[PDB]
Image: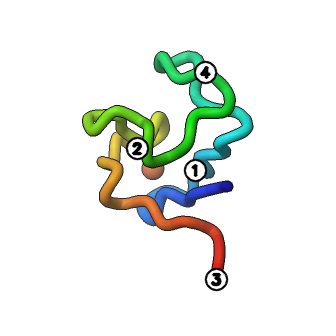
C-alpha cells in the first residue's frame, strides 16, 4: 500500500520503505516505529492517510 503525508505530499510506499532512515523495503506503515516521521517535513505517523477507499 501507499500512504500520503497530509502535510507535505510525501508518499510512504511500502514497496520502497525508507532505507535512508532505517526502514527496509516491504515494511508496512503499521510496522514503522511509533516515532518514525515523514522524511520531508517531520510530521508524525498520525498525519498520514492510506491511499485507498
Ligand atoms: Fe510530510
Q: Dividing the image into 4 quarters, which one contains the C terminus? A: bottom right
Query: What is the x, y in percent for residue 32?
Result: 42, 36
Residue corresponding to mark 3? 53
Residue in the image at 55% along x and 60% along y = 4
Residue in the image at 34% along x and 33% along y = 33
- Whichever of labels 1 and 3 marks the residue nearer the N terminus, that label is 1
Question: Can you tell which mark lies on residue 23?
Answer: none
- Alpha-carbon distance for marks 2 and 1? 8 Å
| Labelled pair 4, 1 in contact (Cβ < 8 Å) | no
Q: Residues within 10 Å of mark 3 (few under 14, many from 20)?
A: few
Q: Residues within 10 Å of mark 2 (few under 14, many from 20)?
A: few
Label 2: state its secondary structure: loop
Question: Can you tell which mark lies on residue 24?
Answer: 4
Q: Exactly how many numbered labels are in the figure?
A: 4
Residue occupying the far right of the picture: 15
- Alpha-carbon distance for marks 2 and 4? 20 Å
| Labelled pair 1, 3 in contact (Cβ < 8 Å) | no
Q: Dividing the image into 4 quarters, which one contains the N terminus? A: bottom right
Q: Nearer the viewer, mark 2 or mark 4?
A: 4
Query: What is the x, y in percent for residue 30?
Result: 44, 47
- Alpha-carbon distance for marks 2 and 3? 25 Å
Looking at the picture, tell me which residue is in the foreground, 31 or 37. 31
- Whichever of labels 2 and 4 marks the residue nearer the N terminus, that label is 4
Ligand 1 lies under 8 Å from the Cβ of mark 2: yes
Q: Nearer the viewer, mark 4 or mark 1?
A: 4
- Whichever of labels 4 and 1 marks the residue nearer the N terminus, that label is 1
Ligand 1 lies under 8 Å from the Cβ of mark 1: yes
Residue in the image at 30% along x and 48% along y = 44
Residue corresponding to mark 1? 10
Amino acid at each position: 500500500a501507499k500512504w500520503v503525508c497530509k502535510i507535505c505530499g510525501y508518499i510512504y510506499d511500502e514497496d520502497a520503505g525508507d532505507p535512508d532512515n532505517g526502514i527496509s523495503p516491504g515494511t508496512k506503515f503499521e510496522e514503522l516505529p511509533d516515532d518514525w516521521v515523514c522524511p520531508i517535513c517531520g510530521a508524525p505517523k498520525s498525519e498520514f492517510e492510506k491511499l485507498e477507499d
